[PDB]
Structures are given as C-alpha cells and as structure tokens.
Amino acid sequence: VRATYTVIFKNASGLPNGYDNWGWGCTLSYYGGAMIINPQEGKYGAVSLKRNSGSFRGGSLRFDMKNEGKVKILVENSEADEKFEVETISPSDEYVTYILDVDFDLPFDAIDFQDAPGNGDRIWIKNLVHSTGSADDFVDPINL
Image (cartoon, rainbow, N blue to C red; front, side):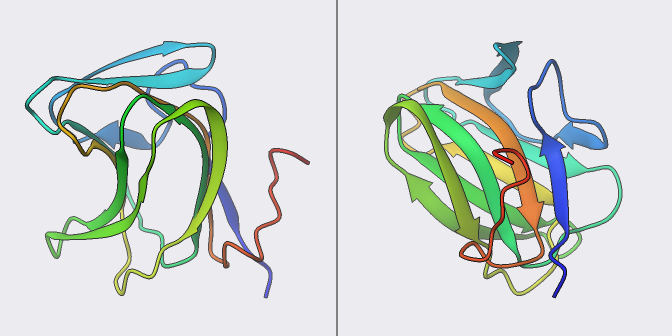
C-alpha cells in the first residue's frame, strides 16, 4: 500500500535523465522549465519518452500541460510493440494538472504525448510523475 512515486521531470532543461525521445515529427525546446513540443504539421508528431531501462506498471500519470490543440496521451511496451491510449486532452491556454489512471495490461517503458489533430499545435509539459497507485489515491509530491 505504499505508493511509489517516480519523478520523471520537474522543470526541464533537456530530456529527462534516464530517458530518450523515440517519437517523431516534433521539435523540442526548453524554456520556463517546460518541455515545449512543436509538432510538424501533417506528421501527427509525438514525443515518446522512453526509459533507458526498466518499466512501469499500471498506476497513474501526473503532469502539468498547456496545449493549443488536442493531445493524446499513450503508453507503450516496446518489446510487445504494444501501444495503449490513456486519454485525450482539450486545448488549454493555461497549465492544468492531470492525474490519470493507466489501465494498460502490460508494463510500459515509454510515455507518449501526441499532436492528435496533426495540425502542428504546441504542447508544454512539466512535472511529470508516475505513481504505482490510483489517480484518486494520488498524493502529489510536487504541490507538497
């Protein structure tokens, strides 16, 4: 019953440590401690934050986001070549915190953020954290 919290990044100046980006169709920059994703129009660009080793299982994904477009959140097992949609998210001009459950039936070593319309709309992310526990049971280490 002790939830484990894994802080993937708080403020970003570059890719999170222990991670690579295996996505496509995006340019990435970093200001204000945000990971700023700029998808190429037509590509349905995605960032795929892929663990150097290891996997998560179920749990919840917490993160702040602002986004000029709809954003798909997925997770992937890259051995099973299996993807899984977690949620889609409406445009927001300001950062909203999201804590979402991951009902994926396998471990996942990659966490994706995708330009769902393919229109090239920017995405800002901060404070990405995984919990082995539920979203409702999430006690945020970052606000704390």
